[PDB]
Length: 143
Image (tube, rainbow, N blue to C red; front, side, top):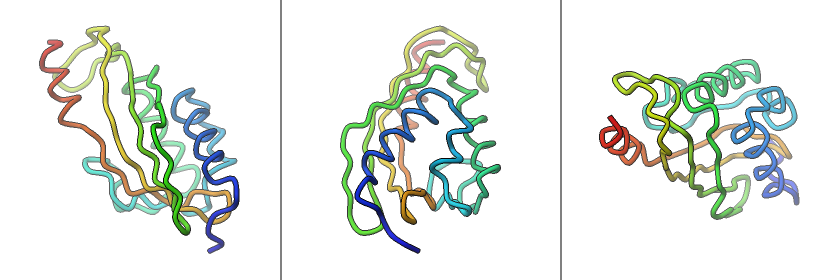
């Protein structure tokens, strides 16, 4: 593939904003490559899978539905070669019922790091770690 363009960081920033923070699922069409691989993403149902844009959008829909007002707050962008690593904080209201923890309305906070791989301006996959234990713990204190 092509590796990054000069605008990789700006692209991730907009993509994260539009798709992930604002839930503009269809904006994925502007950012996702024809093949997108969830290279690593602990507990992600799509981990290890190669998705097409449609499949990618379905995953966004599932993840967004869990915390519909979720917002990613990019902390750092670290570009190297065909990748840009994004570190981020995340906030969402616990307002949807999830397994064992019904909607409490409290703020859930998480942080994560995501290596995004590029083919030009398009994302080909991610390698991600998030503070799921932190969320798990916060949900325990909520209920």
